């Protein structure tokens, strides 16, 4: 998992990853890696 976005922080990973198809979201190596359903 993990979407094609650019995080300044993990908090902004929620929305785009939720739209992507996952539940939450964390900032990693510039990516928003999340946990799905």
Image: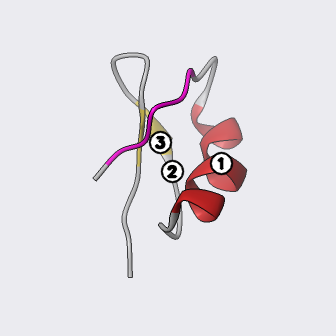
Estimate the x, y position of residue 35 in percent, counting from the top left. 37, 64
Q: Against 26, is 31 above or below?
A: above
Choose mark 1 or mark 3, whichever is in front: 1
**Residue 9: horizontal and vertical position, in percent?**
61, 26
Q: Which residue lies furthest to the left in this view?
A: 1
Mark 2 touching mark 1, by CB under 8 A? yes
Judged left or right of residue 11, residue 27 is left
Q: Is 7 within the magenta?
A: no
Q: Residue 26 carries which label?
A: 3
Dominant secondary structure (helix, strand or loop) of the stretch shown in magenta: loop
Name above or below for residue 6 compared with residue 13: above
Q: How crowded is mark 1: few (under 14 residues within 10 Å), some or many (20 or more)?
A: some
Residue at the spot of label 1 = 16
Identify the residue at horizontal 65%, vertical 61% (top origin).
19
Element under disc 3? strand
Percent of width and height locating residue 18: 61, 63
Residue drawn at 54 percent across, 29 percent down? 5
Q: Position of residue 7 (x, y in %)?
A: 58, 23
Q: Do the residues labelled 1 and 3 touch (CB within 8 Å)?
A: no
| Circle 2 residues within 10 Å: few <14, some 14–19, many ≥20 | many
Residue drawn at (40%, 54%) of the image: 34
Q: Which of labels 2 and 1 is toward the front? A: 1
Secondary element at tag 2:
loop
Distance from Cα at disc 2 to Cα at disc 3: 4 Å
x 67%, y 41%: residue = 11
Region rendered in magenta: 2-6
- Sequence-wise, the earlier of marks 2 and 1 is 1
- Kindly state the secondary structure of the residue where label 1 is placed: helix
What residue sits right under mark 2 in the picture? 25
Figure check: 7 above or below 34: above
The image quarter containing residue 30 is top left
Given contact means CB atoms under 8 Å apart, are the residues at marks 2 and 3 in contact? yes
């Amino acid at each position: 998992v993990g979407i094609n976005v650019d995080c300044k922080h993990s908090g902004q990973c929620l929305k785009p990853c939720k739209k992507a198809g996952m539940r939450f979201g964390k900032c990693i190596n510039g990516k928003c890696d999340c946990t799905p359903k």
